[PDB]
Image (tube, rainbow over the protein chains, first blue to last red):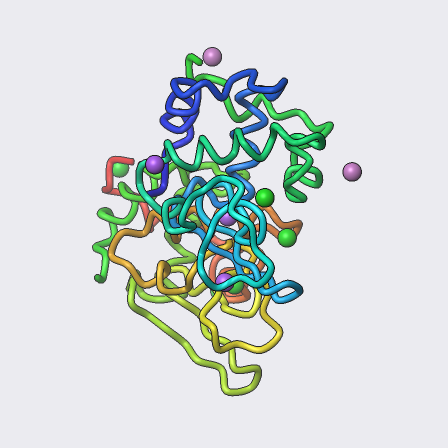
Length: 130
Length: 130
Ligand SMILES: [Cl-]
Ligand SMILES: [Cl-]
Ligand SMILES: [Cl-]
Ligand SMILES: [Cl-]
Ligand SMILES: [Cl-]
Ligand code: NA
Ligand code: NA
Ligand code: NA
Ligand SMILES: [Ru+3]
Ligand SMILES: [Ru+3]
């Protein structure tokens, strides 16, 4: 599913993302926008370590979800990676939270570092009433 | 699916394309028309570099989507090029938004520049009530 901007913000806010471990709703919006285009079906293979990023947050098969294809893997979210390719994003929300409870926080995602960090991101929630 | 002209103008307008990065609805229409004749199933293989342009916007598998058969690929929309052949263009629109956020914007499609840039394109939207 391709969420609409304000529809995703309200969905993420309903599930407690706004302010989570310090992270504003807008920064989650920005991450998802550059990771997937708000598309729960996005995917991206990584040839360096033969892992794959899954879903609306591009969560990686090495450390966070099991896809049965990735060497040296752990399943820190205890999820089939295919659970992160589903129209319902409750599971993906739970796994993004689990990712950011580690020390480096939202810095886990490179694209967030390059596209969102230290940048104005109000554009993501302006006019959504959240 | 081959869109009818206004059908596509309403669809693209509903998916937020009017004014996106300053790109008019009319210009997106002119891009779709010269890329694929509004045909969601259009594909163009290039035996030169073995890449393929997909769907209604003819997005290329070397830079933007993964079709698992193009050398030197980077999948910047984190998307299967199959998603660019759907009747539902929601994945395609989201990927086209990612394309024009690069520094060249819409100028990425050489056809748009040969056929649309600096030209009158009001005829693509008028009568469509958009
Ligand atoms: Cl990750
Ligand atoms: Cl392209
Ligand atoms: Cl990139
Ligand atoms: Cl002329
Ligand atoms: Cl009119
Ligand atoms: Na891929
Ligand atoms: Na879920
Ligand atoms: Na994208
Ligand atoms: Ru940095
Ligand atoms: Ru507001």
